[PDB]
Length: 294
Ligand SMILES: Nc1nc(Nc2ccccc2)sc1C(=O)c1cccnc1
Image (cartoon, rainbow, N blue to C red; front, side, top):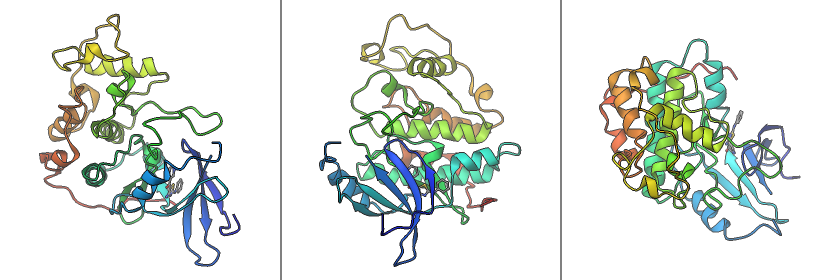
């Protein structure tokens, strides 16, 4: 736009493109997300405009929403790096546990806030978590919900990452609960610790079976109602559960205990963000500053 002197492209989310841009008059640097559509509906702005009144230190601030010309531009405060890039940069040495703990704690604070205000993220992944030089981490790109996963991709031809998707979604549940966000965050937590994605599936069934191979194929005992799920098949292979000592070494018992509660199959048994903040794992939490190379 003529209002922004687009600096550079910084991403390709799942609904459009994200640019780093400067407000020619204010001189502010922001992240400008363009969204794709027979004139772009208006039943979205209502829930979008809501996200705008959702301010928390661990949530990327949505500054402006502009529909004009039937295109929809989202203007967010700009952060210099995402967690995916930081994880990659920290691959050889690993993110120090104290920083891993700080980030997890802040993200749970952010989710606790969203959830208490009936807002679900729905698509948490490293690329959607932003960090700054001050040690903060913030939730971004709330998948804007749109329709709980609809359409399905950006707008042209991109391969959506399934690695952080909760089992109930993969089994066809039509109504997501706040529990889906805790699952994704648990997966991210594991990844920061081991430096390898926990469940790197390449298709919906491979994603589901990677989960089953590690946590055991769910049954009515651990997940009441699972065999009645839309996409559940009695023909699913029956895998035995593995121990967390083997899944996220060398994370300590407090860490493993918290992770196990974030990864419970039954959405109803999965720990809430609020309850997770009280877990003994955070007894000694602090706020370290990351070594950010910008
Ligand atoms: N505010 C913000 N800053 C960002 N900064 C940034 C800096 C360096 C590399 C990549 C992103 S991204 C970003 C976003 O609101 C966002 C993120 C992911 C999908 N859609 C929108």
